[PDB]
Amino acid sequence: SVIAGVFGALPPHRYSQSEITDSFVEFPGLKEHEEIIRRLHAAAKVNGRHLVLPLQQYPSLTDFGDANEIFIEKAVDLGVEALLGALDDANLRPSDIDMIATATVTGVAVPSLDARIAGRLGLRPDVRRMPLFGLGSVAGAAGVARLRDYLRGAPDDVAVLVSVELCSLTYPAVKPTVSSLVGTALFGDGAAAVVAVGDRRAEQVRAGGPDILDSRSSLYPDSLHIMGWDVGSHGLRLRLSPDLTNLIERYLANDVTTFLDAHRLTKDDIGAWVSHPGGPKVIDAVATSLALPPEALELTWRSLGEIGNLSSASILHILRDTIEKRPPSGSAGLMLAMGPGFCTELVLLRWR
Amino acid sequence: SVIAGVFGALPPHRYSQSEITDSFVEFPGLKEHEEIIRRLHAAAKVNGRHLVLPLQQYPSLTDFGDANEIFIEKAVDLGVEALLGALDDANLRPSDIDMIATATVTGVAVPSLDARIAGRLGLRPDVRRMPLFGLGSVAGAAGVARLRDYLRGAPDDVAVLVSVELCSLTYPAVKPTVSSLVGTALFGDGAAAVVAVGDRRAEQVRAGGPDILDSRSSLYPDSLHIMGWDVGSHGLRLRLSPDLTNLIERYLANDVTTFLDAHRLTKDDIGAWVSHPGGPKVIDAVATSLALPPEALELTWRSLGEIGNLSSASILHILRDTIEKRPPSGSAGLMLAMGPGFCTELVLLRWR
Ligand SMILES: CCCCCCCCCCCCCCCC(=O)O
Ligand SMILES: CCCCCCCCCCCCCCCC(=O)O
């Protein structure tokens, strides 16, 4: 399992953070909350976000069915763009793909995104499909890890993960509640794709990106309420408990120590950290938990600032950033994500 | 990859097809359509179905949110019942599980079922999770196929697949339009679970089920409209094209020939067929397109008649039935399913 390509895609409509806010407080039913909205938006540490729709169109997006239908169309466009890009980076072709996995939590599609995506790209009719849905924000790391699991038993194959998250589209379910307003300060739209190859196929594809060495999932007891969707007539409504950061602060070290002990590594042996940008308070929690220097998580901070929180797609944008800035050849890399479960996922990388 | 435990779980309320038709024509907004309903319900070759709610409660199930909530409450219950039954069948404990795959098209759960099930039965906090959504009626075959894919590269491991379909809970989306009435004629509620182990683990636990030898997907081009959902404020509205059978008759024989040749096998080599019970027209098409004697698909016919179309769970019930019938020791087994995509999945087995 060696990564051969990584690529991120973004919708063309980009808006500065306060632009978004300036219009948002004026949306129907939101002006009674200008103050908490401005505060929450200014404290998100996001400087701009890409929106799959013109900012001016969101107030009229009140029907879940309308929103989901648009999701299905845009999601497939962006996912195709990402996959095509990651294949370019790997210098590979659609026909070479033996297994495709898709991750999203922001739309409901049957047939799944992989069926549609594979239809658009002219993938082998016999390609193996794997649509993950319930995973959310953790599916970027967990998805890379599922690639390894597959390629571990299929050493000559090529596998891809595609992650599309169009968070702006969940708007119909947004209420002037604290947890939904937090989601309104953090989340943006985007996609990302990873092309990965088996051990036997790496050398003759000239697979560049890092090896995928291992992963470990960590599912916390009695924590369903930390992250989720309240699903209904209104669509997909965010559940976000305050206890989230406290959870990370109390258990994240053990997740990390248990996994690295297994490889006889310490936190110090990590050459590059690739963390999910849940938001200021969550990034702080990770740094505090693992006692990391301000520079360890700077590419995730940077990511949060430039494109916001992209659910599962963010950890892959950041991963691409990390690859570009060429970490020490042969050093360890750690992917660290968290999502609905509650769970965390850790992936072990080795930079080339 | 060797199967070691299979197990079906059903809701307590069983009703006759006629008990169901009789109350159903009297449901709100339905009496005007009694003729077509009685015609459809009789022609389905379903004699009874298990329902997760008391028959007479459905007229009041009009809120997609209420239905999805109920789906989550009940799906987990049924899910852990099936898994437990398969583990006991396999003489294994929940802590032995290394990866759990979940499959449903009938509810929207974030956190997913596998997380909820894992929390319930006490799976290891580090169990691998694979939440498959959008495979629909093919997820029974496909799920077994991804179990091989996982165990192929983990010969000491245990991986489980848990299917749960509560079709009756999509009632809020139902209206007296044709394809939706066809649905009310065929679909029932239920769940199933498969427990499989790696080759090396096989001898230790003495796995008795069939070997999982190979699989082949077959995605049909430009056929996304054949079946799926139309997701909206009202939930999950069925899309079922009339063209479905014609695609089966046109291309199924080839799907199987290309797949069997690769093993130097002929239809006549197959000792037991485990086919998805789409409904009468579908079963016939399969029998017809291939050249199968009436007895070849009888277990499918019996399952259809006995508990309805359980979506992805059916072929696992039918697998359970087949295992019990004990086909020729050492003979070939072939699973065949079809679903949203449009696609088919074939899985080669070898009985003991
Ligand atoms: C223009 C509006 C943008 C903000 C979007 C509205 C609020 C979205 C709230 C949730 C969106 C993304 C949530 C994903 C969480 C997860 O990955 O599990
Ligand atoms: C009284 C309620 C009886 C049952 C009502 C059935 C409503 C029809 C909808 C069921 C559709 C299930 C389709 C799943 C299979 C698939 O999508 O591939």
Image (cartoon, coloured by chain):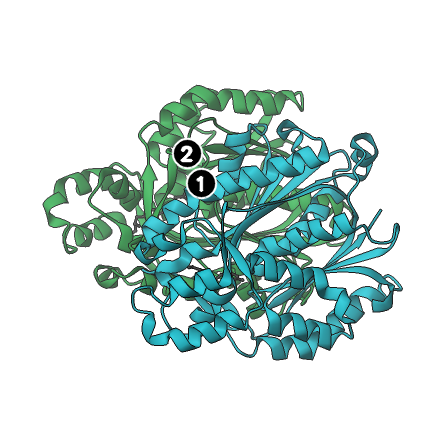
Chain colours: A green, B cyan
Q: Position of residue A277 (x, y in %)?
A: 41, 38
Residue B120 x, y percent position in the rendering: 51, 31
Looking at this view, is B118 or A248 the one in front?
A: B118
Position of residue A223 in the picture relative to residue B322 (left or right):
left
Residue A322 seen in this snapshot: no
Residue that badge 2 annotates: A224
Subunit that carries the residue with mark 1: B
Disc 1 and disc 2 in contact, CB within 8 angstroms? yes
Name the residue that disc number 1 marks: B111
Q: Is residue A3 above or below residue B128?
A: below
Instruction: Pinpoint residue A236: horizontal percent, then vertical percent.
Output: 34, 50
Nearer to the camera, A338 or B255: B255
For the point 58% across and 55% down, the residue is: B312
The kind of residue tagged 1 is: Pro
Q: Which residue sits at x=53%, y=24%?
A: A255
Label 2 neighbour load within 10 Å: few <14, some 14-19, many 20+:
many
